[PDB]
Image 1 (cartoon, protein in one colour):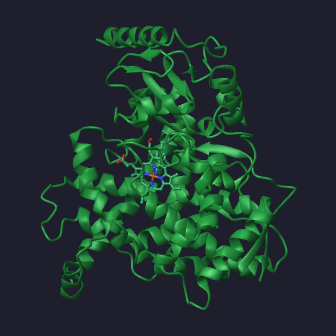
Image 2: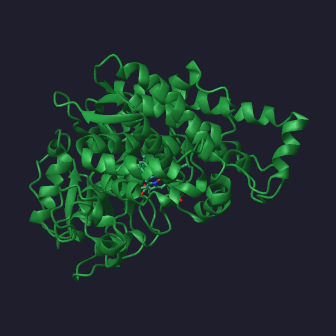
Image 3: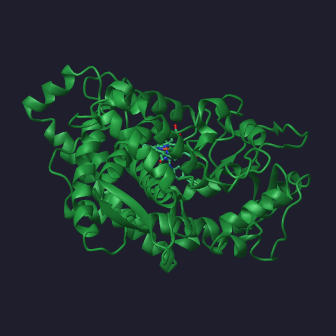
Length: 482
Ligand code: HEM
Ligand SMILES: CCCCc1ccc(N/C=N\O)c(C)c1
């Protein structure tokens, strides 16, 4: 009985280890594989030095039973991430208790169904009205920030940006009305923190990899408590909207619109979806999009404002660009976001050096041959290291240098299409990319018009992976009103 399970395990690792025989790599500890380096602070930068020692790719082991091929070169990236192979179950299985089998984790033709269902929810006609909402939520955040700034001390902006991103996500895509944040929404935010802290730690800690053992550890119990808290939040948001649509005034109003917001699509009002969702399939897409359409943009906004603080020259250039575009308008219009070409460049360079998602994974369903002759069989595990990809010395002159002009029209024409993929690429790219970009542009444009941002030399951020890219100590900045 149990004997089979242990043998199925030991065969898999000789399979994975032999398929990577073509690929030299760093030294393994006998028990931990590479885990003792990965768990060290700064390990993203350690992986970068590895990519210079080993071109294209190198193996990566958490504790001797699971072995990934870390990849970080554009042809290698493209060979795999253009194909739609499944997400790595060893990594993505951990998601299930929390966000379930929603879009992120699915892989079948069921994935294509949901992707087809949900993609019109991020069409630009659905997005145009969100610009006003981004502005309102940002205004609330900035009024808080104005009070903190005139106290003269630096403070962590990450959490305030998150509360704002969560509120705006819910007003846009989950039907929440103008009421704004409630103490129960903050409960949810805190729980996401615990979920991503713990699940990242689980990814890196091979002893927690087996389901049965993990749910008996304090770690796993803490995770399940947070999963309940996340589910109490999403059950509420679902019941709230179903009930709001029982009102005859609101229900007729939604039908009139050609374009439906994301939660209303899932609820299949108008019968148009033609695909019937289980109660749990819908709970999972809500869980999924409630993690995804806000934790990442919080990382992005916050690392950007840090990059503005580090580089006042570019900060001031962006401040001037957005000042002219707004002119005398009350608030930015959707049409205005395309004019923000220099803000966009700086934002792209921010995402090169501080990718909001630094690492994603796949398990191949078919073999793949790489531009240099090497190859892998089906069954093998891939680790796309977006962090080291964006820092690759054969692709990026002076990789550690912040230079927005790398994303001018001129210096972009030649560039390889898989060199810069912070929203991934291929069939499993980010469904929310244009949502994020428009949100982040409105938020940061308004931030720079109302404050000048300085770093704090005594508390510079330190990089911390937590599924999204966070900081060990927050993002502490000084703010000057204007
Ligand atoms: C949900 C969701 C997906 C899955 C879409 C699908 O599978 O069809 C998605 C994908 C990605 C990926 C790939 C994930 C992987 O390889 O495991 C990356 C790297 C990424 C990065 C960012 N996303 Fe995203 N994303 C989903 C949802 C959202 C939403 C939802 C409203 C927004 C907004 C958004 C934004 C960003 C983002 C912004 C800074 C980054 C980076 N994503 N997504
Ligand atoms: C398995 C480690 C990374 C998994 C992962 C994949 C996608 C997202 N987000 C995508 N858009 O928001 C996050 C936040 C994480």
